[PDB]
Amino acid sequence: KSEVAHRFKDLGEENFKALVLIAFAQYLQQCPFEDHVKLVNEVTEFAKTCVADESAENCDKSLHTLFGDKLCTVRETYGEMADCCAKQEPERNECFLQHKDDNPNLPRRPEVDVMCTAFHDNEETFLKKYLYEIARRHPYFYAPELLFFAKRYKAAFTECCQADKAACLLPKLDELRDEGKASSAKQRLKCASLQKFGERAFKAWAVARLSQRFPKAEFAEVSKLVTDLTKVHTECCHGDLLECADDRADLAKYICENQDSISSKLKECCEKPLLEKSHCIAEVENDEMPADLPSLAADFVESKDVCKNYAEAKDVFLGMFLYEYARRHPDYSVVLLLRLAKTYETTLEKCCAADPHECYAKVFDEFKPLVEEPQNLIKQNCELFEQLGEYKFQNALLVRYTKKVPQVSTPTLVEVSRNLGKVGSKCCKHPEAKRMPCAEDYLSVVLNQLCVLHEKTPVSDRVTKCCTESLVNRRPCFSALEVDETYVPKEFNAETFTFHADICTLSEKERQIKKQTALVELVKHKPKATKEQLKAVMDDFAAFVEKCCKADDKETCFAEEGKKLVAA
Ligand SMILES: N[C@@H](Cc1cc(I)c(Oc2cc(I)c(O)c(I)c2)c(I)c1)C(=O)O
Ligand SMILES: N[C@@H](Cc1cc(I)c(Oc2cc(I)c(O)c(I)c2)c(I)c1)C(=O)O
Ligand SMILES: N[C@@H](Cc1cc(I)c(Oc2cc(I)c(O)c(I)c2)c(I)c1)C(=O)O
Ligand SMILES: N[C@@H](Cc1cc(I)c(Oc2cc(I)c(O)c(I)c2)c(I)c1)C(=O)O
Image (cartoon, rainbow, N blue to C red; front, side, top):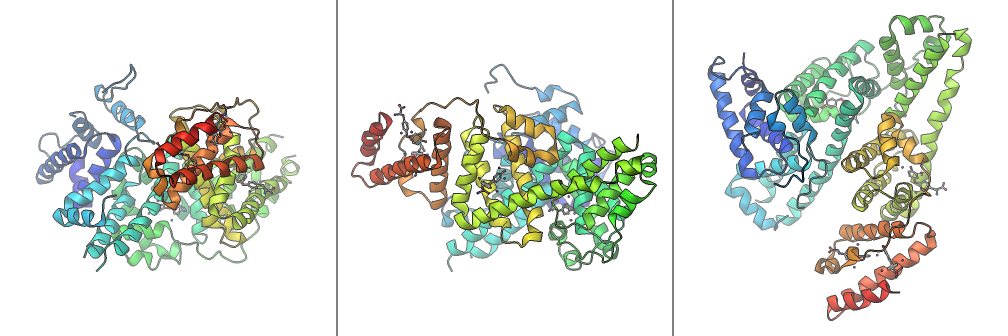
């Protein structure tokens, strides 16, 4: 009779408190740390009263009613601001969801010895700081995976803080934020899929992906798994985080009890601890594909029953087409497989209302150009990457995309282009047959970042079109954009280049980011400059910066010499 009691008992007090803190920090990203912990503790102690008697006052209230009521107990609007706390459920929860900010304007690592002192001072307060700061900067983070990150975070300190601490803690902390931002972007795509294109689009994506990983499983087994996984991500993406974690744990138990009807690669994943086992299953490699599978053309092109099966049970028949095609093509990206199933459905739509056997007899010819376009694209960029290396590969992609959509803001163009260029590092080391799913599905994740970053403040009609027209065609849409000829050159400002004392002591990574910022501004100012012309200007300006960083009075040099180039 009490839902808060049910989840407190299923998850245990430690994971309960952590998940409630994550939930509050994702809904109110600007609220100070001390105010959230205070609300968390009141919630936890009420939950204990309900475990002791599920008929006590208020113990019958929904989780949304209880969490929303707490958040409503604690500046300038410029005339525009939604008032979520004046709404009733379920409208109030929808209002909270609509104010999640993907780009929180919030500040961006103290000394190694300084952290170690705060750790042993209070471990528990130190770990909650880690959850709070990540959750408020990534408001769609997959909440059960964040628990697994917090445990690896706790283990790095419980080892390195106790000969040298810097050479022990800093490499580990560095892979925790790489692997942290990869995980965040990956889940932002699932949530955008469910919220903008609907449940039916998500389930197709999951049929395709689970059929590749589990090609020996029966179609009925894949469909059960997809139904359970869709419920989990629906919950995590609508802020039902206690339910999401409880159902994720239940799904892992089901998979591990039924290994022999699912995959032979699960042996070791299923012997690991609670959070580690779900994380293991999520990244398991594909199983071996059965030999001598019958031809696809036999059931889907040649059978005289094609139009009958499409009419009598359309969702099952089209789901079977996708399952059968995907299990025998681990070498295709998920979005390519979804494009083929859409083409097949359109064709039967047309042909079954006409000699249909003759109408759709040549449907496989339509698939060949869909397969060839991404194969050639990724063959070319890998050639370029191997020649140029990551930094200059990034700069090649940055000039291309700035010229496609020059209205997009400079920070967003730099961040997206850097991430697009990481695809060569990540995927070009694989042999041919392994490259398409690695590269084209990573590119979907980065292009979705461009879409959600731009949606907050739309300025480019072309970005809006490609992001709203069709989820699976996003990458071909962007690849096809030419240079905008209607863009008026941006005029010089100069505030971009004002001296700051930190520019003469940059790390290598932050040097690249400064140079990439200046290249975007240059293309926006001179959209017709050739490649040789851009290089000559770039190389002269970098030499100016190196000159004045060696001066007796740095600021004087920057001010005196910078003005000459401005009036040149
Ligand atoms: N490269 C893709 C492939 C992939 C997607 C899903 I969707 C999936 O099914 C699960 C099951 C559980 I349990 C999870 O916690 C999650 I997250 C996904 C599995 I196996 C693999 C990816 O991993 O996204
Ligand atoms: N030297 C090549 C020209 C070429 C330039 C770029 I820059 C490039 O990289 C991308 C990456 C993405 I993602 C795109 O959507 C696009 I369009 C281009 C590729 I591949 C090829 C030739 O002449 O064959
Ligand atoms: N105004 C900013 C600091 C800032 C100063 C300069 I001078 C600059 O311009 C370049 C151009 C090239 I080409 C380089 O290789 C480098 I390093 C810096 C940039 I971008 C940023 C602030 O207040 O923080
Ligand atoms: N005297 C010109 C103004 C002008 C100043 C600069 I300094 C400049 O050089 C750069 C180099 C980089 I690198 C940039 O990102 C940018 I924006 C401009 C250029 I070309 C033109 C006029 O009044 O028309």
